[PDB]
Amino acid sequence: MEGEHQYLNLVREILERGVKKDDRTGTGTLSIFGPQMRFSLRDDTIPVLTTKKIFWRGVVEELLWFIRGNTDAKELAKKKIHIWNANGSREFLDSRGLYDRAEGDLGPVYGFQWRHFGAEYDTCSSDYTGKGIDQLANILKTLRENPDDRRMIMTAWNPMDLHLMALPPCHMTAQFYVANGELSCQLYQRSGDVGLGVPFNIASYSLLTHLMASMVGLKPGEFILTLGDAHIYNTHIEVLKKQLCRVPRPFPKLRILMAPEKIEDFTIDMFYLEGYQPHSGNLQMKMAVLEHHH
Amino acid sequence: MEGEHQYLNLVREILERGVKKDDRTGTGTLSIFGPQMRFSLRDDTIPVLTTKKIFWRGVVEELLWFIRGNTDAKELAKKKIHIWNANGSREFLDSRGLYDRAEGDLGPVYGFQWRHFGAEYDTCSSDYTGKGIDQLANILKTLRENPDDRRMIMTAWNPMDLHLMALPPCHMTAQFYVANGELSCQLYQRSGDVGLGVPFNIASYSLLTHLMASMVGLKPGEFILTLGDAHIYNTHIEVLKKQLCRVPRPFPKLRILMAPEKIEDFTIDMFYLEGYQPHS
Image 1 (cartoon, rainbow over the protein chains, first blue to last red):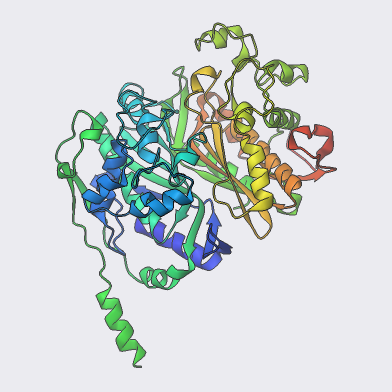
Image 2 (cartoon, rainbow over the protein chains, first blue to last red):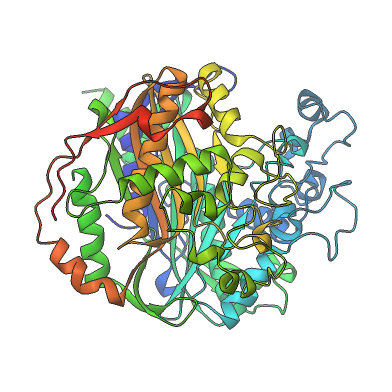
């Protein structure tokens, strides 16, 4: 089934057939390996879940921060995006043997790889202009000049750099593909928290694909998310069973007002979501209170 | 579906709905993006296609060569495995700007990345003992010690070294996973020649999974092949439509007579296929 049903069906598969495993800290999960979801980006569609409210402004500011090749959690915190703060904290960096790292300095995580792959990392505020392999720039050019290319790979998976990172990347490799004037993206995510990180990854990479299509005169096509270890934390099970009861509404549309000459110069003002109408869950809570009584 | 039916269905889908694209040279393909297939390795099964005869000996000798970390096409050619000879030729190396490279020296392709990731490449005959990141050794150790780990990644996609390679890798990244004492492997293949390379990759990474399970006291679980650009060349179409008319037979079983102490010391004599019955 299409659209949001690909996500809900994944949740159900893990609840019903997942294996009882443990993570790094010994907290309980249900787990399967290798599932895939596919989302249309046609007719301006952007797969932002309707069965719960996604933090859209967080999706955008994180993605633009990636695109700039930035790695300072403090720059997101200034925009009131706090999702990277815990990974940049003194305690977290210390637990990874990053004793000489300033608070907020995540190291060469996603963005740095996207724009500066193979460069030597100094701090999150050093000037990395023309350093390393600009994977994202290379793909944009290839999309303009030779869109049939089968090597349009962007990876954050550098085994030399993993020990310098707050955490090893999980949305780790993407491939782009063009057919009939349409740009598709597949993401390989080795580890996906299906209750929390995965809905965010779907919105984030779908947005990246709409933005990249802008840059290169193509239309958006599909976003494919392929997972390694797809898991649900035991603490989320009950909330996710209630989410599965909620009928999806149509996905919102992304409206782009302009595209700048360089993709790192996108600002949040240049595009918006039209028709985003997520569940609040109030009607379901009312029916639970009413049904209990009978 | 069952294993081989997933391969035949993928072929049907590309012939039926694929897009008319071109490759590097401008030679025609039909193409889709993002298909997946899944093969059970339970009960000793190994997905070697029955609807045509796979070059099993070529599968094994190429895989062992990868596992040793070797990159000399001439070592394969000595065992009458010639699948790498064209990419190691004077003409092909020159077309890549590798004018200083001895014939058959492919550079730091697949196996060098598996066993020596990040080491400086000299020639295919240099001694790379204890050089670079031994990704494969790290995973086998993680499998014994911490089989729930979610970072059991092996990659050949090293952007720094792509220009040194006869070809950029297409079977580029694998992940390993364990549940219930079973070892599963997912391969990311960015570019699959569905008519020729893909049946090979399925046999190769399925064999790798059986062998790795051997080394670490686990049973084989599944192999998942995830494609990027999955394509059929125009010249393979007639032969593939005839292959689709053949009813699959049950997959062979892999028998392992022994596992050596180190995975790079496996030889073809240490395992075989039992009950392989392909169509002629």
